[PDB]
Image 1 (spheres, rainbow, N blue to C red):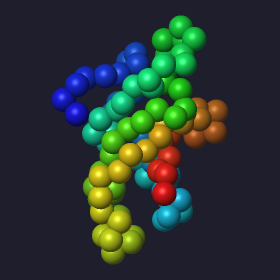
Image 2: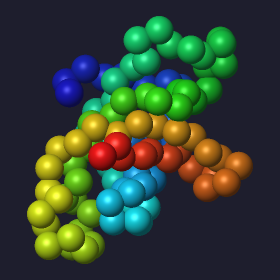
Image 3: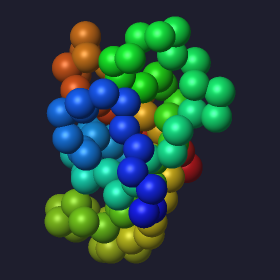
Length: 94
């Protein structure tokens, strides 16, 4: 997580993480991001593509909606939907 990686001037190290388990979307800070192995970007140089792997801690939400039993560092996939949410979105796989 000590390696610094980003696309080009992203808003900040935060993404709207949708948790299917809780059925809630909460913006969490991104602890670390992992590049796409082949980088499907067609010289776009804007934002990363869907399926980008990030590492986030599902505990710092502070909402406490699942008794804290869900507390664990998990990997989520970035999926930017600026036309719908207007923000960088992330989805948690279960």
